[PDB]
Image (cartoon, rainbow, N blue to C red; front, side, top):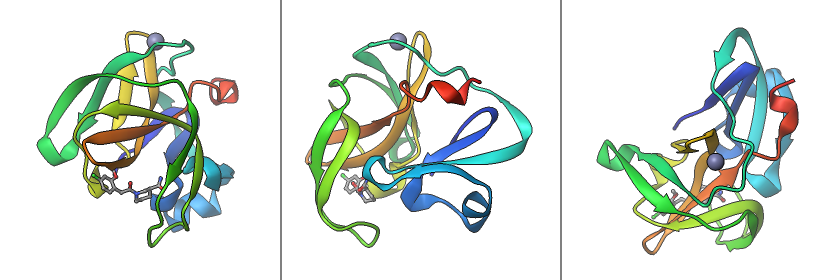
Length: 139
Ligand SMILES: COc1cc(Cl)ccc1CC(=O)N1CCC[C@H](C(N)=O)C1
Ligand SMILES: [Zn+2]
């Protein structure tokens, strides 16, 4: 679990969104595993606007932050689950690192702010759903 709170928005993994998130839906994209819902209170998380390929992510399964090098946002094949059939997930970035299913939602950050959230993993790899292209999160 885990979410990004910026302005009047909440960004979460689409597969972990709540009834409240869906009743306050702003935008969702199955192909990216993202859902954005509206909030009454303000969020102060700074979203990075950069092409950083290094950063730090939070791993709840280890109660630790890990530094990682990560790939450019791209279309990567992701195997089936109780949430999705097997498909290409877009805007996905991989790093060599530890993750487990309950790690989805952990934030990846660079020196410029929030880059994205944990969305996939397996085989010593961890995948992050990029959010740096969602320019409207600030305005
Ligand atoms: C961090 O997630 C891990 C990690 C490991 Cl090692 C093993 C399994 C998972 C879970 C995972 O990748 N899923 C299930 C939830 C939806 C995801 C998606 N974006 O399509 C795919
Ligand atoms: Zn950056």
